[PDB]
């Protein structure tokens, strides 16, 4: 995640193993139950896309759901690209590039790039955009997996 | 176990089968286009006659929540 | 691992016992399952070759796989030496030596040497080269151990 | 138990035997060259007739994934 | 152990209880298995002789092995004294004394003395000398306790 | 399970039923106004005759502590 250091700057720090394991354990115990979404939300505080793929990729089991989510993440990403067209002409030397759906999904962007966008002024909340897609896709799952 | 060996039982819920499919698909490393081909093809083909019948009625263009709710009583 | 200190320099710090044990427990519980690879990747963040041999050497069980991996690590290392020939003439006093496959595998290099290469400017990512060999060899295993 | 005492059963999968071999090989401390000699030699020699037959057909130059997939039905 | 402080000096800090307990638990679970030696090696990082006797003395059970090790430690120590004779004439006021086998075993030396030798310039690696004796004696045990 | 399928048993305490209701209501994602409509309507409707009778006597304007204490002996 990207956290604030004592000095008063935003720097990246790694997520903790008993945080990781707590994510694992939630999924083990409460599967598709709604409490998973606030839980997720708390444990995703200050998290990167990269950390969010890590969390999704480290799941075991419920592979039908994991595939449905993936496909929702790509749909929501396809929709990001649709709604926000690429911008006019070449990229400025003085500036950094606008993200695509795949940069938001973490796929085409690097960590330093993910830190550029979030730490820069104005900052862009690529975590929160992926977060809604995850929560939206979580609703899809919850609604389906209701019996 | 190979992906071709993944098939739906005569009493097995589709759901439990679809889970098995994307787990084994999860251990296949092929290009995405090939894995898309496997998705639309092999899943239905090794599905049981009762659900297979059901899935034929959904037509093409169908998505996983609709397939999964479609074969629920079977 | 080699971590950044508060002062703003990269220094080595030892890996933690409940990190070690978490590595052990993953292997105990999920054996050859794919979730092992992201899991590995997270727990290998900022890790040395030396720490990576420690993790491999501390395995118990699955010795056929452990041997297949070893032999993959040496093949990938043999390939490193092939692709990157040794350089022209004697080593400069002002400079430090280029690594071989066995330095990447941690075998012929010392820790201080592993810290020289990574901390120096430009830095060389000998962890990430071993990491791909481990991940590649993990694919070999996963594909075989599929039933 | 000594490394010479490691042998494959008549019904034991090779796989379970190869695991036993590199565990015991893991408690041998000899030079690498000697341990290479042990690998190519003793493993096949104490392998059962049915797999032994199989392994003779792989010829030399063979690697562990190919040996391990070669004696799978045995 | 003797660790580097934030200020940039080498100072002694005590070993942790869940480190201690992790040492205990390894021995409980894996007895004489080879994985014990890398495990030992990691948990002995930056350790003193004094801490190494603490670890050996805190064992319960396997007393035949513990005695065989002791006797190996004394043999290896007797050998240290043999190979390295005491030096010519009286000890200088400006200098500190050379170690014997029993100083390496921690027996005749005090902690402050163990910190003098290791922190001083040149430093002498009395941990690493005891470590080889421990590892050597571990090989003896492993080879015997093979069935 | 659908919200319409939530009903009170003939021997089931209301309390255990109300818990089931706001759990299932917790998995409904509808506008608040609709969920208010569901609250005043469906809860009483699928309540058992003995408590249903009781709840009719509370009249409208009633709140959950008063409903919950009202059907306690039933």
Image (cartoon, coloured by chain):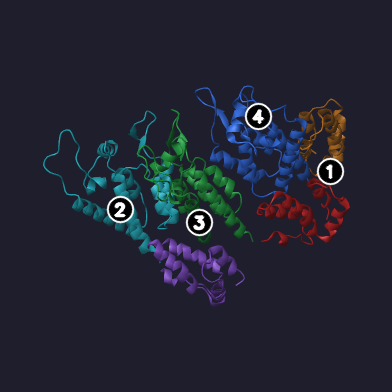
Chain colours: A blue, B red, C green, D purple, E cyan, F orange
Residue occupying the point 71% across, 41% down: A33
Residue A8: image location, x then y, percent: 52, 22
Question: Mark 2: few, some, or many residues within 10 Å (few <14, many ≥20)?
Answer: many
| Chain designation of label 1 | F
* In the depicted structure, whether residue A6 falls above or below residue F4: above
Question: Mark 4: few, some, or many residues within 10 Å (few <14, many ≥20)?
Answer: some
Q: Which residue is mark 4?
A: A97
Compute the Cα span from label 4 to label 2. Answer: 59 Å
Question: Mark 1: few, some, or many residues within 10 Å (few <14, many ≥20)?
Answer: few
| Chain designation of label 3 | C
Can you tell which of label 1 and label 2 is closer to the viewer? 2
Residue occupying the point 46% across, 48% down: C104
The local secondary structure at tag 3 comes to helix
Q: Which mark is residue E65?
A: none
* In the depicted structure, whether residue D18 falls above or below residue E13: below
Residue occupying the point 61% across, 38% down: A50
The local secondary structure at tag 4 comes to loop
The local secondary structure at tag 2 comes to helix
Q: Are marks 1 and 3 in contact (CB under 8 Å)?
A: no
Q: Which residue is mark 3?
A: C75
| Chain designation of label 2 | E
Compute the Cα span from label 4 to label 1. Answer: 52 Å
Residue E86 visible to the viewer: yes
Number of marks: 4
Can you tell which of label 4 and label 2 is closer to the viewer? 4
Q: Which residue is mark 1?
A: F5
State whether discs 4 and 1 lie on one chain: no
């Amino acid at each position: 995640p990207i956290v604030q250091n004592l000095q008063g700057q935003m720097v990246h720090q790694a997520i903790s193993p008993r945080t990781l394991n707590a994510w694992v354990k939630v999924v083990e115990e409460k599967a598709f139950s709604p409490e998973v979404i606030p839980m997720f939300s708390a444990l995703s505080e200050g998290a990167t896309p990269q950390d969010l793929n890590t969390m999704l990729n480290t799941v075991g089991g419920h592979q039908a759901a994991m595939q449905m989510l993936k496909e929702t993440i790509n749909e929501e990403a396809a929709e990001w690209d649709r709604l926000h067209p690429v911008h006019a002409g070449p990229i400025a030397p003085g500036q950094m590039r606008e993200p695509r759906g795949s940069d938001i999904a973490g796929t085409t962007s690097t960590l330093q790039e993910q830190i550029g966008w979030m730490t820069h002024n104005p900052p862009i909340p690529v975590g929160e955009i992926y977060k809604r897609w995850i929560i939206l896709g979580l609703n899809k799952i919850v609604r389906m997996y209701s019996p | 176990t190979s992906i071709l060996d993944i098939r739906q039982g005569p009493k097995e819920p589709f759901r439990d089968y679809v889970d098995r499919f994307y787990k084994t698909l999860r251990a296949e490393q092929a290009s995405q286009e090939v894995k898309n081909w496997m998705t639309e093809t092999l899943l239905v083909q090794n599905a049981n006659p009762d659900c297979k019948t059901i899935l034929k009625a959904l037509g093409p263009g169908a998505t996983l929540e609709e397939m999964m709710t479609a074969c629920q009583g079977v």
